[PDB]
Image (spheres, grey):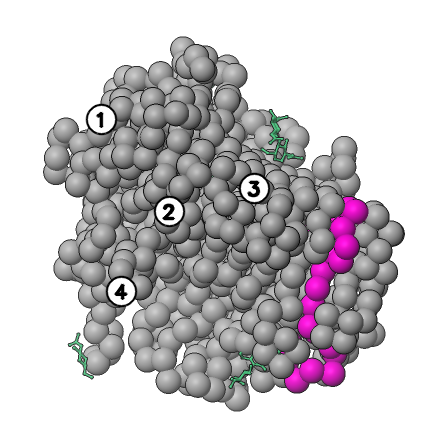
């Protein structure tokens, strides 16, 4: 096939990792420049693998690395492969977006999967610790297993962590062989996700075999699979806009049986299970001692599917199909008339969860969604390269004025293109309310300087997105925001603009990465942990003030956005060793929004990871947090002073008279103050340490409190999982749901909180 003309294939390549010492390292690789023929006849395995591995990248024996990113581009074509495509650390596998190429497994293909994102060596050790396998894309492919015997074949071994995505992939598999068919689209053994969007699975035994701590996956279609989704294990998982068609089983979540369920919780929203034998197989019964197997259905059609939910241990139909299920919950519920203050285990349909119209797509009535833009129809001439227009991206030069001048002059038909590099910002950059910005494989935008962002008593925005009250169209994608040295006055992104329409203002694959990597000066040398002393709280190890602030009137659509304060060092010489980085606050949302967050995560801030203050119209699915591992050395009262301008939590006051005082002063996973119409569909809010000691896990008591609802906040929580917090949820100062009353297979889990 002809080249597609997609801008990405032809845009001038001027990028380079600023902190890789090799001036000739090449981030972009077109597989055909490595000898791939793309005709489906010549075996292209070696050429594709060489395009990935070229340049001394992070493969076997390399724990992790941020200075060897790669964007591996596959022009339109068919690529015959006979062994796995090994995706090295920090790789974007980018098929052509206009005409997604086919990865065609040879009949004699051998190996784990057509694409392997985390190989096992001969001794059974992964190349990368699964929970550290960050910063990846696979997008725009057809993966064809149909030449392989039905007894073998997996499309992608997707064993990954945060800031990863699968997008726009079709998996074509055989339908013959009965019980001996073993083909599957995704094979996922474990990990810590992550996002998937816009996938189609045709045939096979399983569309996907899934096992992971937590994941958000939406707009998935399954056609003629035996079981569409085999959920092997999880803590939580949120599915939205899933279409299952003519399968034997939709979601199998009964692994382990009624006395050993390995699936923690599943949420299924805005979905359709059509012409399928059994919609969902579960082993849950409300008399069981634990919360394993929790399930939420919200707005799910069951057309032509006579058994919507089946208890496959007893064989009993729990919910009849051939009707829409407005809402179903099984697991423990609190609040309202059903659960009350003590909580109650239930397995029942119930009344619809009504969401405000501002959060919905008016065309479908589903919660609004929009995938990461790839600008397929935009000509290369419309892209304005920052390096072509005066920004150096060298990680030292002050690029503030050059970037500001680009932002001030770019027209709405153009797109600002951040060539890969590291762009030092030394004072506030004002982003206008009409702009589109996209990056070459996660360029770094770093708050730097020696004064402007240094004062936590007088914090300042790094990127100020619109001015207060403005409406417009602002899109950013494929970028990382961070600090160069400590910048405890930096508000990394202040989001003032509101979209003209849903999805017109947002962030896709845009991450805030505070410390831990080359260029930050916040690495193992400077910030190594020392739990054996009282922490000095080194000034050289502070991070930012606040990673994201949606101010009153701001409205944003966030999808695949990781707000991460480093718990460990990311370059290979450090061997994943742990560090202390002191970052005040994660994500703060105020005002009437709306705000959507799909597949967001906020981890290791001191005061809170997510906070809603005087907020309305917030939809998050699913969310994930961690407390910083150094707490309580120091505890959450240090080193950021309480600032009422950000409604900061005041732990010295709030923990007064705590019955569990030793571990009370710890970062909030989620805090809501005077906020309503907030909807959280799935949450994994974890506390794994106390001053790097994990003894507290044995009694699920690393911290005292995890979610705080204050000022009669109406926060509608579904599939809330928390790890090792005595109290999962506290309302107006009273502990409501205790971990001990809601034990799952690892976390504790509340299916449904009625506010
Ligand atoms: C769900 O994802 C699928 C897969 O990307 C989308 O289907 C593609 O839609 C585009 C735009 O119409 C077409 O050009 C492609 O041919 C489609 N691909 C396939 C495999 O069908 C689909 O649009 C998405 N649906 C929603 C509601 O977002
Ligand atoms: C929920 O998960 C827990 C943890 O896996 C299950 O408890 C385990 O059950 C297995 C039997 O399959 C035992 O071998 C383990 O010793 C148990 N561990 C603990 C910590 O109790 C529990 O049975 C599951 N509950 C339900 C209702 O499925
Ligand atoms: C803290 O003490 C332990 C002994 O339990 C030791 O192994 C570790 O190296 C010490 N840490 C530092 C930073 O010295
Ligand atoms: C609490 O939220 C309401 C909106 O329901 C708002 O009118 C009120 O001003 C808020 N209270 C404070 C103290 O800001
Ligand atoms: Cl993404
Ligand atoms: Na302008």
Inter-mark Cα distance, 3 to 1? 47 Å
- The answer to whether the residue labelled 4 contacts the one labelled 2, judged by CB atoms less than 8 Å apart, is no
Label whose residue precedes the other's in the sequence (3 or 1) = 3
From the viewer's perspective, is the residue at label 1 or at label 2 nearer? 2
Q: Is residue 731 magenta?
A: no
Query: Who is closer to the viewer here, 317 or 598?
Result: 317
Q: Secondary structure at mark 3?
A: loop
Residue 453 x, y percent position in the rendering: 30, 46
- Residue 319 visible in rendering: yes
Q: Secondary structure at mark 1?
A: loop
From the viewer's perspective, is the residue at label 4 or at label 2 nearer? 2
Instruction: Quickly name the residue at label 2.
Output: 110
Q: Which residues are magenta?
A: 269-291
Residue 96 x, y percent position in the rendering: 45, 25
Q: Residues within 10 Å of mark 1 (few under 14, many from 20)?
A: many
Instruction: Quickly name the residue at label 3.
Output: 173
Label whose residue precedes the other's in the sequence (4 or 2) = 2
Q: Is mark 2 within 8 Å of ligand 1?
A: no
- Counting every numbered tag in the picture gives 4
Instruction: Quickly name the residue at label 1.
Output: 392
Label whose residue precedes the other's in the sequence (3 or 2) = 2
Label whose residue precedes the other's in the sequence (4 or 1) = 4
């Amino acid at each position: 096939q002809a080249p597609s003309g997609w801008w990405l294939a032809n845009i001038a390549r001027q990028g380079r990792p600023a902190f890789n010492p090799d001036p000739n390292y090449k981030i972009f690789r077109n597989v055909k420049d490595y000898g791939a023929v793309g005709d489906g006849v010549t075996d292209d395995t070696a050429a594709i693998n060489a395009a990935i591995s070229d340049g001394n990248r992070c493969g076997q024996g390399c724990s992790s690395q941020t200075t060897t990113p790669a964007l591996v581009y596959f022009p339109p074509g068919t690529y015959l492969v006979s062994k796995p495509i090994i995706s090295y650390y920090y790789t974007q596998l980018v098929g052509d977006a206009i005409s997604p190429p086919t990865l065609k497994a040879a009949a004699n293909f051998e190996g784990m999967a057509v694409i392997d994102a985390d190989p096992y060596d001969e001794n059974g050790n992964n190349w990368w610790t699964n929970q550290n396998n960050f910063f990846r894309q696979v997008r725009n492919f057809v993966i064809d297993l149909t030449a392989m015997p039905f007894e073998v074949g997996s499309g992608i071994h997707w064993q990954v962590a945060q800031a990863t995505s699968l997008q726009n992939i079709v998996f074509n598999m055989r339908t013959d062989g009965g019980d001996d068919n073993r083909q599957q689209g995704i094979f996922m053994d474990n990990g810590s996700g992550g996002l998937m969007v816009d996938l189609v699975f045709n045939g096979g035994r399983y569309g996907a075999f899934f096992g992971n701590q937590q994941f958000t996956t939406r707009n998935l279609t399954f056609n003629n699979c035996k079981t569409a989704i085999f959920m092997n294990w999880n803590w939580a998982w949120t599915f939205q806009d899933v279409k299952i068609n003519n399968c034997e089983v939709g979601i199998d979540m009964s692994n382990g049986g009624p006395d050993g369920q390995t699936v923690g919780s599943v949420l299924l929203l805005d979905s359709h299970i059509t012409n399928t034998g059994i919609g969902i197989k579960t082993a849950y019964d409300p008399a069981q001692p634990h919360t394993n197997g929790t399930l939420i259905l919200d707005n799910v059609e069951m057309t032509g599917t006579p058994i919507a939910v089946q208890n496959d241990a007893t064989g009993t139909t729990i919910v009849d199909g051939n009707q829409k299920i407005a809402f179903f919950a099984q697991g423990r519920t609190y609040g309202g008339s059903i659960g009350g203050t003590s909580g109650k285990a239930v397995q029942t349909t119930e009344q619809a969860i009504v969401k405000p119209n501002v959060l919905l797509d008016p065309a479908t009535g589903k919660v609004f969604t929009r995938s990461r833009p790839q600008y397929e129809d935009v000509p290369v001439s419309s892209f304005v390269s920052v390096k072509a227009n005066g920004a150096k991206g060298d990680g030292v030069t002050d690029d503030t004025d050059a970037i500001q001048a680009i932002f001030d002059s770019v027209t709405p038909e153009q797109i600002v293109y951040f060539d890969h590099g590291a762009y030092i910002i030394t004072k506030t950059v004002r982003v206008p309310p009409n702009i589109r910005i996209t990056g070459e494989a996660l360029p770094l935008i770093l708050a730097g300087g020696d004064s402007f962002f240094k004062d936590q008593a007088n914090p300042k925005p790094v990127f100020q997105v619109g001015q207060p009250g403005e409406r417009g169209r602002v899109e950013m994608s494929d970028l990382i925001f961070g600090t160069a040295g400590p910048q405890p006055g930096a508000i990394m992104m202040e989001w003032n603009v509101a979209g003209m329409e849903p999805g017109a203002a947002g962030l896709w694959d845009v991450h805030t990465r505070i410390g831990g990597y080359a260029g930050t000066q916040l690495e193992l040398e400077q910030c190594a942990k020392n739990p054996n002393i009282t922490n000095p709280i080194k000034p050289e190890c502070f991070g930012s003030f606040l990673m994201l602030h949606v101010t009153p009137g701001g409205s944003a659509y966030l999808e695949n956005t990781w707000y991460w304060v480093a718990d460990h060092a990311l370059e290979p010489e450090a061997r994943d060793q742990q560090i202390d980085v002191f970052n005040g606050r994660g994500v703060l949302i105020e005002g009437d929004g709306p705000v959507w967050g799909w597949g967001t995560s906020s981890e290791h801030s001191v005061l809170h990871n997510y906070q809603f203050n005087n907020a309305r119209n917030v939809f998050l699915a699913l969310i994930q947090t961690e407390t910083p591992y150094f707490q309580g050395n120091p505890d959450a009262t240090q080193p950021f002073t309480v600032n009422p301008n950000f409604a900061d939590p005041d732990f010295a006051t709030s923990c007064t008279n705590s019955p569990n005082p030793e571990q009370c002063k710890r970062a909030w996973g989620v805090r809501a103050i005077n906020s309503t119409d907030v909807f959280i569909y799935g949450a994994g809010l974890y506390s794994f340490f106390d001053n790097y000691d994990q003894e507290c896990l044995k009694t699920q008591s690393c911290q005292t409190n995890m979610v705080s609802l204050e000022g009669n906040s109406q926060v509608h929580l579904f599939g809330l999982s928390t790890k090792a917090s005595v109290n999962m949820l506290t309302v107006d100062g009273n502990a409501v749901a205790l971990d001990a009353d809601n034990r799952n297979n690892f976390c504790a889990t509340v299916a449904w909180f009625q506010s």
